[PDB]
Image 1 (cartoon, rainbow, N blue to C red):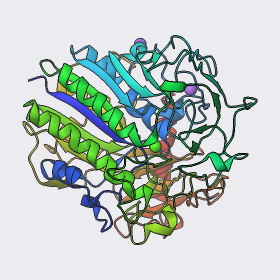
Image 2: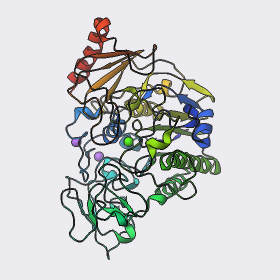
Image 3: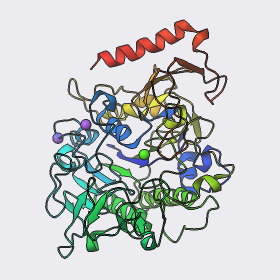
Image 4: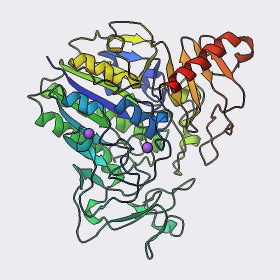
Length: 484
Ligand SMILES: [Ca+2]
Ligand code: NA
Ligand code: NA
């Protein structure tokens, strides 16, 4: 009846991190219930194995690798989605939906890198790309500034503690994680992550001031979840689109005390529990307001997982049997399947049958055109150019695979998934991530082709055996790049 649409997008949540995807080590009852009430997808792909390019593509319907700078965004990047670029929020606006973006961003603010006046109004910001309401973290949790932005101004701005940010130069007189580990009363770094100190945890980049506007990590989930509930409640009488992007499970993991210290995988496990709690809070509010039946929830993750992403939180020591990538090789940053094959759940009780498990090959690039079909919007010519309408497959009304899926690795090496085949194009990249995480990249100077029917773990390179399959996969990348 113009259904509401909520995208719940986790950060760095792996295929294997949720209980309903097979781990013995963490209880995720709210997400398990959500899946039981709809579809659990086993073959959904993000477009990229890193945060910024993945989110760029799902919000614009354009592969990030078409646009210079989407894969190397500065710590204080300007807007990566420019106001001239058509977004999923613009699409919903044109169906007379109220639009909101709450939580994690990864996509820049203001005009050019470093030009944000944190003591004033930021512009361009999310209202310039179609979001009526926004309450976002200014930066991901391991970066500065550690403040929230509400519609283009700093939330709870403190004029007694004016804000300054630099990714190039420290502020004289401010402590740093490297110089002053005695001030890290909550959490110490592993690799890098040893610059500004906020809330007893060091960060990437330098900052001064903030005062009352500075976040506390243990309250981030509560804060963003509360804002998501308020957006739903204020819009209970009209169609809305909410893009709810959690901080969890991004580093630093430092969850609320109702969770912290309770899961034996350590703070990383507690962050999965906290994610599940946030999902439960959304589900409870839809039930309280009688919105459950006519609300489409799409829950997924921007990219695959990482154990040690910069903090001394014992993630590797305490993982035990828990495989964040599920059956897949690699992780965040990688060209291997754990980089882009992510959890994905759809619940929409009016239209989607309960208790389904579907292996349909699908890509997040298709959300904008698929949801345009749902809400009867014709996207203008040339806009969302890589997005295809697969609404029937996303709602389990069809089992038709996407003809192929394109995956972008951190080095911009592209891969193709087509039926059972996975092709990785050659690159000069290192076989391991070099800066801290011990993640296999799948970078190699020769063609790689894997039969995912024979093993979900990409171990046996069949490229030399099947030149005709390699040529078809390479021809797909030529065709995709030629649309530029
Ligand atoms: Ca991410
Ligand atoms: Na860019
Ligand atoms: Na715009």
